Image (tube, coloured by chain):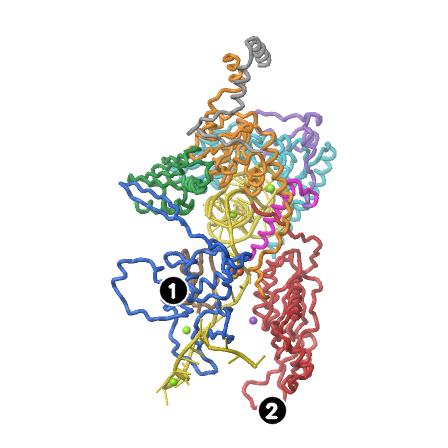
RNA sequence: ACCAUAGUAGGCCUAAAAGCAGCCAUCAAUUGAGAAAGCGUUAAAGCUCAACAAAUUCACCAACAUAAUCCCAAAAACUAAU
């Protein structure tokens, strides 16, 4: 395996793709699941 | 002889045998790269013996340790490992900083107290950072603060 | 090849290195399995001080010789090449590899005396005032012993001391 | 100088150098170490 | 202008050797040291050696910092012997238990030499054992009063034999 | 490092080093930095500040020096060797002093 | 004239109290605690002679620690013929 | 970073009492009142006595032949005693005390009359005979340093040699004799009496194989 | 090249013996460094060499003055040699 390329701040434009897919997965949920997701996070954290 | 042996191709290369000392460094590097969450590299600079010992004492106050490994047994090990991207940082003189429960707020402050001790980079929790990344990581809040604000934004 | 440029611009000095394109080795050598460059082209025991085309590839632009580490020659051949370059310079060959000194060229001196195969240096040999008879004869050296292994088509050994 | 047969370094700062067809022991710290091969 | 390594008794700075010629050579009067060092420590008994660091400054002023006593005095006092063994290894000067070495470790753990490095407790005790190797005092796992008492009598007899031998040795050299 | 100590670094005002450690042609810059930041060179004037600027995508390993006379010596060391950089730095000290 | 202070000679107190530890005038002798309360690592060190070269193990820094010391001894002996 | 090579361990070597060299008398206790002929065959040719190590591991090998008298013994004894460690070094003589008388007639007199009076005593030494043998618990490099000084001042040329070095130069004197590419050798020509060469050669040249001429030994001749 | 910090003036010894008259021992901090290999000090201090790291052409050894009437064939490193 290999690690990341260590992007710099001179041309910082590429965000991690794992974050982006988490945004899409979160946005793909109903408001009822928002409360369930919130309550589980509050209980754990 | 018809042809001088120097001009002839070299004989088959004898298999070099790794001694105990070399193998001892191999596992220690593996150990220090396994159970430690923060691995900060630095350019080792020839300082005063009293000043060097003082730096050890000051880093001891924050549970930060520093070790030195020769490139003869470190470059081949990191090449086969998952931290191969740190090879350009291990070309010349180097110094390694090791810490548990990473916290660079008290580490950069000591580094900035001496203007001639560069901070090249390092890997924090399997993530390679530059000096600017370390500075941004220093100003960043802790896990409890960030996660505590995470639920607020959601 | 790399060159260093130093520029003075208003009490500010700028020093930078620029890379110049370098000629490469010829594609097909007759002996690909050789180690050192001399024996890779079957030039072993086949060059002399006259071979300017060979000695001009292992010398600096100002008459110096490149180190053995960069060239890769074996120690045995490197000394022979070093000896030939010294003999080549004294022989009058390689006129473009001398340093340039505009002030020193104007005051001409005694005309150069043509010479070749000079083992020693012109300023470090003393006259043989007492030569001696045949049973104890002081022989003037010519050439170098490092070149006694060269191929002899005639078959007679080279007369190094005469 | 000191005309001698075999050249030896009396101190670690002596450096060998071949000039005028002979080997000379030249020393910087101690001038008394100057030796000349005959 | 430099550093001076001097061992001085607690509050007993004499206006002579070895303090006089050494400290006065750099340009510092002894009467200054008769007040600074003597007042520096007043709860420490005199006669106990104290390795002190003196930093002489270019303006002929000085700074004093006091460290823990030497290992030699601690082990000799712990073993109850007035001096170390003349021939280390051949003879044993004193016998001490592991408590004496372990207890000394805490006292020296705060010394500027060891406390600065933040050495573990196991680090100091090994050094004391190593110092005891050349001091002539053997570390003992555990002993009692009678075992220690027997060593004292044997050591006294051997010391008495050497004490009278030295007097005879000095007489032979002078007469001959 | 030993050469700079004997030549008197007291006439140097400020030295800064800007390099990208993740590049390939910065090894020479690293060697220059360690030589000028040695203990012997430091113990010659207690006012000069040595600055080790570290970047990632700068792609310009450079060294800037200011002498007491007021000249600005800046050499972008990317192809130069460590010996060349030290020799040039040492040469200017004698001339400007 | 400068001599160490007089030391205790009673075997009972020396075996139970370390007199040399207390250097303060106002201090007192520290009483010996039971050996059970003492940490176990102080009863594990090499009381006797130091470890030889063979008692150590090649897969241990102790062997290389001693071998490094021996190399200096070998180099020092060969340097006895220095003319400088 | 380098390689920590193991160091030699010397624990089986025992230092005998009085490790320093024994004093040698100038004249043997019983003088020889009869003057004998000055044999020169005791120098010519290779040595047959004391050619191998007995106790020590270092010795001075005599490449040539010559005479040793009381003066040379003092130089060898004093130099070694003041340069070695008595605790780690012990030395042993490999040559006897001077026993062969040497005659010197009076200064400035006509030839004749007879042999003169005995002047001093010498010890004949052939080629390949060890002179002083030293052993101990130390490496050869430091022993070689102060042995070449003693070997240089001997009459015959000599070297400081050890157990490993002596075997290497004897194992190379055979390889150089086995791989020789010259069809003709001194051993072949002399023994077979080729070219009538026996008229020029000496009867001792059959055994010497051409490696010995007078008292001089040339090790490079095959 | 580069680089030097711990116990610790180790015990003994001596007027003073701080790695460095001698005797004795030769353990031990630190990833790394010998109760010391050399120099130096009245004794200290100090310089240097081994050990850190850095880094990697090769490196055993081989040096020896002069005579008397005026030096003494001239000269030549390759056209083919049992
Ligand atoms: S290695 Fe073949 S001639 Fe150089
Ligand atoms: K001789
Ligand atoms: K001493
Ligand atoms: Mg150790
Ligand atoms: Mg070193
Ligand atoms: Mg003369
Ligand atoms: Mg003539
Ligand atoms: Zn010198």
Name the spot of residue E146 as percent of width and height, x first.
Answer: 74, 33
Determine whether the beta carbon of the residue marked 2 sits less than 8 angstroms from the nearest atom of ligand 2: no
**Residue at disc 1, CB closer than 8 Å to ligand 1:** no
Colour of chain C in the rendered structure image: blue
Q: Is residue H32 above or below residue H12?
A: below
Q: Which quadrant of the frame does ligand 7 lie within?
A: bottom left
Q: Which chain is red?
A: H
Q: Colour of chain F?
A: green
Q: Quadrant of residue E128?
A: top right
Rendered image quadrant of residue H101: bottom right
Would residue H67 be found to the left or right of residue D5 on screen? right
Q: Which chain is brown?
A: D
For label 1, count other residues whose C-alpha is less than 10 Å away and answer few (under 14), some (14-19) or many (20+): some
Q: Which residue is mark 2?
A: H112
Q: Residues within 10 Å of mark 2 (few under 14, many from 20)?
A: few
* Residue at position x 36%, y 43% in the image: C16
Which residue is disc 1 drawn over?
Answer: C89
Q: Is residue H195 above or below residue F72?
A: below
Residue A27 point in image, percent of width and height: 53, 15
Chain corresponding to orange in the figure: B
The C terminus of chain E: image quadrant:
bottom right
The quarter holding residue C56 reads bottom left
Gap between marks 2 and 1 measured at Cα: 71 Å
The span shown in magenta is G54-82
- Seen at 60% across and 45% down, the residue is G68
Instruction: Please tell me the numbered disc located at residue B154.
Output: none
Chain for colour purple: G
């Amino acid at each position: 395996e290999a690690l990341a390329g260590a992007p710099l701040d001179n041309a910082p434009k590429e965000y991690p793709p794992k974050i982006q897919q988490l945004v899409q997965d979160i946005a793909s949920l109903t408001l009822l699941e928002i409360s369930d997701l919130n309550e589980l996070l509050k209980k754990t954290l | 002889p018809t042809i001088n042996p120097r001009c002839l191709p070299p004989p088959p290369t004898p298999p070099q045998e790794e001694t105990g000392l070399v193998r001892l460094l191999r596992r220690e590097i593996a150990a220090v790269f396994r159970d430690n969450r923060m691995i900060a590299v630095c350019q080792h600079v020839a300082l005063s013996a009293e000043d060097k010992l003082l730096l050890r004492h000051q880093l001891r106050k924050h549970k930060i340790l520093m070790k030195i490994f020769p490139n003869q047994v470190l470059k081949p090990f990191l090449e086969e490992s998952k931290y191969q991207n740190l090879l350009p940082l291990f070309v010349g003189h180097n110094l390694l900083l090791v810490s548990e429960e990473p916290k660079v707020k008290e580490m950069v402050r000591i580094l900035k107290g001496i203007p001639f001790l560069p901070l090249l980079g390092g890997c924090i929790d399997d993530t390679i950072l530059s000096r600017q990344g370390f500075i941004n990581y220093s100003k960043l809040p802790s896990l409890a603060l960030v996660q505590g604000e995470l639920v607020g934004g959601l | 090849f790399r060159e260093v440029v130093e520029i003075l611009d208003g009490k500010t000095t700028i020093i930078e290195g620029r890379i110049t394109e370098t000629p490469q080795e010829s594609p097909n050598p007759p002996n690909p399995t050789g180690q050192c460059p001399i024996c890779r082209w079957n030039l072993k025991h086949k060059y002399n001080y006259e071979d300017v085309l060979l000695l001009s590839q292992f010398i600096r632009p100002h008459g110096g010789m490149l180190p053995r580490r960069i060239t890769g020659l074996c120690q045995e051949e490197h000394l022979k090449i070093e000896e030939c370059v010294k003999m080549a310079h004294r022989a009058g060959l390689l006129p473009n590899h001398r340093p340039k000194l505009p002030e020193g060229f104007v005051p001409k001196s005694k005309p150069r005396l043509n010479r070749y195969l000079t083992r020693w240096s012109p300023r470090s040999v003393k006259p043989i005032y007492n030569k001696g008879h045949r049973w104890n004869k002081v022989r003037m050296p010519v050439g170098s012993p490092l070149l006694k292994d060269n191929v002899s088509y005639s078959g007679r050994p080279l007369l190094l001391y005469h | 100088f000191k005309t001698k047969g075999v050249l030896k370094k009396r101190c670690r700062d002596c450096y060998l150098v071949k000039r005028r067809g002979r080997w000379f022991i030249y020393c910087k710290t101690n001038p008394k170490h100057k030796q000349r091969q005959m | 202008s430099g550093m001076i390594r001097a061992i001085v008794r607690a509050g007993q700075a004499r206006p002579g050797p070895p303090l006089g010629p050494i400290l006065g050579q750099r340009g510092v009067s002894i009467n200054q040291f008769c007040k600074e060092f003597n007042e520096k420590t007043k709860d420490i008994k005199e006669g106990i050696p104290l390795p002190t660091k003196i930093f002489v400054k270019p303006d002929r002023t000085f700074e004093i910092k006091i460290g823990q006593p030497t290992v030699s005095y601690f082990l000799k006092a712990a073993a109850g012997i007035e001096k170390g063994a003349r021939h280390t290894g051949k003879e044993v000067a004193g016998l001490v238990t592991l408590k004496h070495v372990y207890e000394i470790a805490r006292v020296k753990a705060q010394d500027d030499a060891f406390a600065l490095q933040d050495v573990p407790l196991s680090s100091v005790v090994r050094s004391i054992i190593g110092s005891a190797r050349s001091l002539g005092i053997r570390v003992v796992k555990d002993l009692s009063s009678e075992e220690l008492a027997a060593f004292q009598k044997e050591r006294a007899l051997f010391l008495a034999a050497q004490r009278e031998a030295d007097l005879a040795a000095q007489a032979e050299a002078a007469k001959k | 490092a030993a050469a700079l100590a004997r030549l008197g670094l007291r006439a140097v005002k400020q030295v800064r080093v800007q390099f990208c450690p993740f590049e390939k042609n910065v090894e020479s810059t690293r060697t220059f930095l360690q030589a000028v930041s040695s203990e012997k060179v430091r113990c010659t004037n207690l006012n000069c500040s040595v600055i080790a600027d570290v970047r990632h995508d700068g792609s310009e390993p450079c060294v800037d020096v200011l002498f007491g006379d007021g000249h600005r010596l800046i050499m972008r060391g990317a192809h130069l060797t460590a010996q060349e950089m030290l020799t040039a730095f040492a040469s200017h000290i004698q001339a400007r002093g | 004239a400068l001599k160490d202070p007089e030391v205790c000679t009673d075997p009972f107190r020396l075996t139970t109290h370390a007199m040399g530890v207390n250097i303060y005038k106002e201090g007192q002798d520290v009483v010996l605690k039971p050996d059970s309360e003492y940490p176990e690592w102080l009863f594990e060190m090499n009381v006797g002679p130091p470890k030889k070269l063979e008692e150590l193990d090649p897969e241990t820094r102790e062997y290389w620690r001693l071998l490094r010391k021996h190399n200096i001894w070998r180099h020092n002996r060969l340097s006895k013929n220095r003319k400088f | 970073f380098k390689t920590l090579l193991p160091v030699p361990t010397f624990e089986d070597v025992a230092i005998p009492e009085k490790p320093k060299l024994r004093f040698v008398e100038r004249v043997p206790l019983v003088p020889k009142v009869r003057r004998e002929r000055k044999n020169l065959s005791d120098i010519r040719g290779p040595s047959t006595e004391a050619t191998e190590f007995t106790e020590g591991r270092f010795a001075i090998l005599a490449l040539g032949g010559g005479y040793l008298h009381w003066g040379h013994f003092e130089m060898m004894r004093l130099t070694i005693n003041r340069s070695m460690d008595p605790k780690n070094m012990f030395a042993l003589w490999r040559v006897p005390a001077p026993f062969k008388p040497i005659t010197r007639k009076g200064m400035g007199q006509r030839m004749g009359g007879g042999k003169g009076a005995i002047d001093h005593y010498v010890t004949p030494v052939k080629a390949g005979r060890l002179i002083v043998e030293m052993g101990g618990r130390c490496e050869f490099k430091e022993v070689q340093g102060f042995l070449d000084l003693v070997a240089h001042k001997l009459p015959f040329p000599a070297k400081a040699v050890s157990r490993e070095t002596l075997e290497k130069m004897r194992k190379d004197q055979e390889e150089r004799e086995r791989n020789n590419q010259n069809p003709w050798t001194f051993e072949r020509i002399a023994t077979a009496n080729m070219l009538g060469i026996r008229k020029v050669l000496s009867p001792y040249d059959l055994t010497h194989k051409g490696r010995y001429w007078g008292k001089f030994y040339t090790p490079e001749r095959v």
